[PDB]
Image (cartoon, coloured by chain):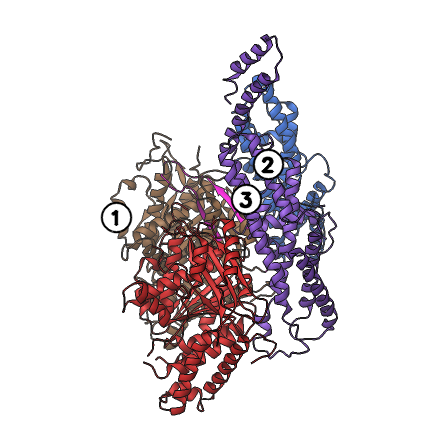
Chain colours: A brown, B purple, C blue, D red
């Protein structure tokens, strides 16, 4: 149904602005809010239908100590949204405490938007893990949202902070945030900073301006993830029906994404399926094996070729995953959007549950434990101090993420009747 | 056609013959001969260019005379279960399934519904029928494709026994390396080589026999431009192939079949034995050396 | 326009229509619309298209609508959740299969021949042959979505596996489900293996 | 079936680079990996079929202390291969010991490539005998490959070090390498340095830059040896079927090669058969007699003329070999490649087993024994010392090569029912 977006963190507000700009360009919308002259397709999930058919984006921007919001302010696209949903230290506990005291008015804004919406389906989160101000306050808001609304869905888009080092206290912050994400979120879309950075340095020749490109990448991914809802077909035109297949168990809810063209500015679907199963098209980094794989195709498709392609790729066994049970690949189809020039119009997406990200989490589990053992890297922050004088919440999150890694490695085994 | 254009001229000549008092065979003959050239030429003109007759001939060479050895090797590599008696209720579908599945690994992502494999052993029942455009070709008949199926079977036999033999050669890989290999009981006079020669030489001979006729046909067709002459060339091509591959019932054909049976039996001996061991192998080996020595002399009658 | 719209008004939008019926009054459903076994269906046919579109065509179309309603019922009913972990595994065992079945009936049949059929009716030159191509569309889509005959080996199998979807929905004892499911699943594959041959598209799954 | 290539030694990596460049030029391949615009022929043995039909060469480069690999690195043809298959003293025992400690990860790379390949047929080796670093490590890898894979084929392309002197310890190294090649290899393709050097000084007027030309020569020879597999006919489109005729006995597995044009930039097949039987077209140096001869022809051939040519050359008796048994010449045919300008399009190759190379081996057996007898040429190398304090492995290899020469000379006799 109707989904409200929340955006917080500097990179999160960047990709939210880019996402809304991308959808305004994608649909028949002017940057004033007015419907375009040449506008069939649904805008009834993320866009409020206002008085002059003004598709006002259903978005709530949360920030504290604004810097980039001023750059949002002086824009022609500052008249598309902001019906006054904008509300004005780099520690987790700092942002937690600051969000604690102003929980009421921002929750009042959320309830205001819930009253403004006729229906409700979910709150999708734009998040940056260990982004400083975004950390802690984002976990706090996630806990509040799970508390107040036990009937709605929570989706999280976030990047995982790895740049091969910087901040000595960020693994603690990301560990607490991951503990909150495991318990207080329903489904998590995971992203890696170094992987997207490497792809940006790969297909292009940039080294510094990675933000401006990665915004485009995440915007394309997120819009692709929502296209079958935005452009109505009839397979999984609800969020919940899509998410139900992707989550095999409530302990594994992290989703790996790709994108079939690394650059799209006339191959068949058979080729790009083979491309997508190659890991260079995969944008998120014993044997690691998928549990369940889904793919979504949008382009110029012949309907017989997808069947024979599934036959041939099935027989070729390019799906290097061994499950513990009956779970298999799932196909889906979406519409190519108008008004956008696309060479090689076939474009696909993948949503798969893969165990390999456990190793990435294990990297942080190694790092944090190392800095815990030497104990010269907690640095004695005061917000961390009165929030927890004994710092046993870090031990609690360490317990949870250990259980999580064990659940991962039990899922790697060909039986999940045994647990980890 | 240009027959419709020159229709009235042939009609004028026929009316002239209707007008004449005298019945002369010589004139009537000339009229018929004059019509016949154009009539054959139009079919020639269409069939070479627009129905792509030569392109189909390439496929015929590929799949009937086994000009594509690559697929019909991996076909045997992935299927060895038509050496046991088919029930012809499940295997019939299965062999065609395995054929196209083997083909899918590389090369032919377009048709291959046109070849049909039918089991009427299972390598002595496997046939092949290629679907041709029936309105667009009358050169091809059921009988022509049947003869193609015959030579297809005969070519299958030799590659089948040879593949087993050459695959069984693992002497230089396993048996000799790191192993001293007892001899003068577990000698076999290196007869693996001796058995290999008489079939491999035959393979080379068959290569020349097929390739010569296929070259001659593809040369002749471009020169002549009438369908009758094309018919002569094609009906000569088949007749050369049959007799030269010794498909005509001769005692030489029986000798060649006996050689193939000997090789097939020899594979069974060397398969089970594996590296150095005595399993009363000498009993079959004695029979084999006697039969081969007797059969080799018949080739000395074929040589003279 | 009428022909395309008709199969868009049954066989998205109708998912919202059925979710209301998931949780009586037949006029209630109309008002909910306008902004598992049994049901009644109705829609008016205007006369200039009623000389091509048949009344009995609505019946054939209605049957596969009922089947599709059962399919979406199964999809949504097992989509009610996201030691006692044991039920999860019975979830994936069942929710996959009905999904895979849904992929076959819907896209491979109701979208292949459906996309073909519009291109066919735009090529007719006469009122008469338009009826013939239409009825020869109906009779074959009534065979592909098999409802005519040999239905005592297939449709009873689909019904009996849907009874498991009823049982699990109540269940959210347990051991008695897989014993049935593996058995009737083996029935399905052992019949559909050589037995028109398009049924192989679920015999390999 | 599918063959993986391994390349080690400086000259071996040179000819591997030249070989892959030659096949990229030969087939419809761009030096980026992309299929050419005008591309029927098989590339499914040495080229992995990647995502954009990228015929990525199935090659593993093995090196230690890289120098020429840096020159490989800065090349437009450094994007054809290297999907990271490159992994970074001149004694046999030094390279043996160094390969000993890092056997595991390179074997892991080999197993990785074996998993990457669907089928497998053989590991073809680019080797330089007594090339310093290549010696010892190459023998070690050959022993490892024979151990781990008893079901696959091993082909060795290598040059034999003779430049008429230089290094006083290289006959020892080449003798140990020859002992390993006799026992741990399935078929050996032998090359001579002075012979190819003499031909290069013959047809051209060079004295120093022999490497750059000899790369071309070996590349042409090796590609010719594989053309009927690369360009599909139907006679011996497997390696094993070709190798089965060439090896008459597991003790004689060294193959003499030629090349019918000494320079090819309209004679008939009859002439060039007579040319090929002249030893000036043969590129590898009582009576010495062939055991079995094979030839491969690629060009503009009339199929009747080859028969009558075989008649006339048979009657002329230009085949100066006396066997002990029934073995004879074998003919084969291959396709002339497109996209390459060739004047005098008829080009042939010969594969024959000839006893004369025994004398060359005997030359080394004389030399090593001489330096063993004076004992001032072992030089007391330390790698040689702790590897073998008594240096009886050299005696072991001397025993084996003596048995080999005796097997050669027993094969020279008109009975091989007696052994040597």
Image coords of residue B147 (percent x, y): 65, 42
Disc number lying in front (1 or 3): 3
- The chain holding disc 1 is A
Image coords of residue D371 (percent x, y): 38, 87
Disc number lying in front (1 or 2): 2
Residue D158's disc number: none
Q: Earlier in the sequence, mark 2 or mark 3?
A: 2
In the visual, does D340 lie left or right of D247?
A: left
Is most of the magenta stretch helix, strand or loop?
Answer: loop
Disc number lying in front (2 or 3): 3
Within 10 Å of disc 1 (Cα), the crowding (few <14, some 14-19, many 20+) is few
* Residue A192 shows up from this direction: no
User: Is residue C94 highlighted in magenta?
Assistant: no
Q: Which residues are magenta?
A: A324-351
Image quarter of residue D79:
bottom left
* Residue D254 shows up from this direction: yes
How far apart are the alpha carbons under marks 1 and 2? 71 Å
Describe the element under mark 3 as helix, strand or loop: helix
Residue A71's disc number: 1
In the visual, does B32 lie left or right of A272?
A: right
- Between A91 and D126, the residue placed more toward the observer is D126
Q: Are marks 1 and 3 in contact (CB under 8 Å)?
A: no
Residue B132's disc number: 2
Who's the residue at 56% across and 52% down the image? Answer: B207
Q: Are marks 2 and 3 in contact (CB under 8 Å)?
A: no
- Between D178 and D114, the residue placed more toward the observer is D178
Image coords of residue D61 (percent x, y): 40, 67
Within 10 Å of disc 3 (Cα), the crowding (few <14, some 14-19, many 20+) is some
Reading the image, the residue beneath label 3 is B214
- Between A300 and D80, the residue placed more toward the observer is D80
- Between D146 and A175, the residue placed more toward the observer is D146
């Amino acid at each position: 149904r109707e989904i409200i977006t929340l955006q917080l963190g500097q990179c999160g507000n960047q990709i939210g602005f880019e996402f809304w700009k991308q959808l305004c360009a994608e649909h028949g919308i002017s940057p004033e809010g007015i419907v375009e002259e040449f506008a069939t397709d649904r805008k009834d999930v993320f866009f409020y239908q206002a008085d002059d058919e003004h598709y006002i984006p259903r978005a709530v921007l949360l920030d504290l100590e604004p810097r980039v919001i001023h750059s949002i302010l002086n824009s022609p696209y500052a008249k598309l949204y902001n019906p006054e949903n904008i509300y004005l230290g780099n520690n987790w506990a700092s942002g937690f405490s600051q969000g604690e005291k102003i929980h009421e008015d921002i929750f009042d804004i959320i309830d205001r938007e819930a009253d403004g919406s006729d229906s409700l389906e979910g709150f999708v989160l734009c998040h940056s893990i260990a982004g400083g101000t975004g950390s802690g306050l984002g976990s706090y808001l996630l806990e509040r949202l799970n508390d107040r609304y036990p009937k709605k869905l929570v989706q999280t888009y976030s990047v995982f902070p790895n740049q091969d080092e910087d901040v000595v206290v960020q693994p603690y912050n990301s560990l607490l945030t991951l503990k909150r994400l495991t318990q207080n979120a329903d489904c998590v879309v995971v992203l890696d900073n170094t992987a997207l950075n490497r792809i940006a340095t790969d297909r292009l020749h940039i080294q510094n301006p990675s933000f401006s490109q990665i915004n485009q990448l995440v915007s394309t991914i997120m819009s692709a993830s929502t296209t079958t809802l935005r452009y109505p077909g009839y397979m999984n035109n609800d969020l919940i029906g899509l998410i139900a297949s992707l989550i095999p168990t409530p302990r594994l809810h992290f989703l790996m994404t790709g994108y079939t063209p690394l650059t799209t500015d006339k191959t068949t679907v058979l080729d790009v399926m083979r491309r997508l199963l190659q890991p260079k098209n995969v944008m998120v980094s014993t044997n690691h094996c998928y549990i369940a794989i889904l793919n979504i195709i949008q382009g110029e498709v012949d309907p017989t070729q997808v069947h024979k392609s599934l036959q041939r790729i099935r027989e070729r066994k390019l799906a290097n995953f061994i499950p513990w049970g009956p779970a298999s690949i799932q196909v889906a189809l979406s519409r190519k959007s108008p008004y956008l020039p696309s060479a090689h119009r076939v474009s696909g997406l993948m949503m798969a549950n893969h165990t390999s990200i456990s190793s990435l989490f294990e990297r942080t589990c190694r790092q944090y434990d190392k800095l815990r053992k030497r104990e010269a890297f907690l640095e004695q922050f005061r917000k961390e101090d009165m929030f927890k004088d004994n710092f046993d919440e870090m031990d609690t999150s360490r317990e949870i993420v250990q259980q999580l890694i064990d659940e991962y490695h039990a899922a790697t085994r060909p039986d999940y009747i045994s647990w980890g | 056609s240009i027959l419709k254009n020159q229709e009235d001229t042939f009609a004028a000549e026929l009316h002239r013959l209707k007008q004449q008092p005298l019945f002369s065979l010589v004139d009537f003959e000339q009229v018929v001969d004059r019509i016949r050239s154009t009539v054959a030429e139009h079919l020639w003109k269409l069939m070479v260019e627009e129905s792509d007759l030569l392109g189909q001939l390439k496929i015929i060479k590929d799949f009937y005379l086994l000009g594509r050895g690559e697929l019909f090797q991996a076909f045997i590599d992935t299927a060895q279960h038509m050496l046991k008696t088919p029930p012809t209720a499940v295997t019939e579908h299965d062999v065609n399934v395995a054929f196209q599945q083997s083909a899918h690994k590389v090369l032919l992502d377009d048709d291959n519904l046109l070849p049909l494999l039918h089991l009427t052993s299972g390598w002595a029942a496997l046939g092949l029928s290629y679907k041709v455009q029936w309105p667009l070709h009358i050169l091809f008949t059921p009988a022509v494709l049947e003869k193609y199926n015959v030579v297809f079977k005969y070519l299958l036999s030799v590659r089948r026994v040879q593949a087993e033999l050459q695959h069984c050669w693992a002497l230089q890989m396993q048996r000799k390396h790191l192993k001293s290999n007892q001899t003068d009981a577990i000698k076999w006079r290196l007869r693996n080589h001796m058995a290999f020669l008489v079939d491999n030489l035959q393979y080379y001979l068959q290569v020349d026999v097929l390739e010569s006729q296929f070259s001659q046909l593809l040369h002749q067709i471009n020169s002549t431009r009438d369908f009758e002459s094309i018919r002569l060339a094609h009906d000569h091509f088949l007749s050369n192939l049959l007799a030269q591959s010794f498909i005509l019932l001769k005692p030489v054909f029986h000798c060649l079949n006996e050689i193939l049976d000997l090789c097939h039996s020899f594979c069974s001996l060397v398969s089970q034995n594996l590296g150095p061991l005595d399993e009363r192998g000498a009993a079959q080996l004695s029979i084999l050396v006697k039969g081969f020595s007797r059969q080799s002399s018949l080739l000395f009658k074929i040589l003279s | 326009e009428y022909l395309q719209a008709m199969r868009n008004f049954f066989l998205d939008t109708m998912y919202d229509f059925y979710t209301s019926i998931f949780d009586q009054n037949v006029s209630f459903l109309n008002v909910q619309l306008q902004e598992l076994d049994g049901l009644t269906l109705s829609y008016k046919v205007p006369w200039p298209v009623d000389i091509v579109i048949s009344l009995e065509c609505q019946k054939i179309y209605n049957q596969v609508f009922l089947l599709l309603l059962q399919i979406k019922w199964a999809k949504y009913s097992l989509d009610v959740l996201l030691q006692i972990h044991r039920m999860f595994l019975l979830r994936v065992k069942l929710m996959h299969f009905v999904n895979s079945l849904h992929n076959y009936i819907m896209t491979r049949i109701l979208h292949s021949t459906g996309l073909e059929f519009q291109h066919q009716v735009e090529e007719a030159k006469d009122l008469d042959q338009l009826i013939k191509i239409h009825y020869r569309y109906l009779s074959t889509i009534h065979d592909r979505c098999l409802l005519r005959e040999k239905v005592s080996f297939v449709k009873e199998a689909i019904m009996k596996v849907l009874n498991l979807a009823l049982m699990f929905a109540d269940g959210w004892s347990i051991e008695k489900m897989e014993s049935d499911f593996k058995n009737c699943h083996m029935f399905l594959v052992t019949i559909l293996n050589k037995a028109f041959p398009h049924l192989e598209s679920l015999a390999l799954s």
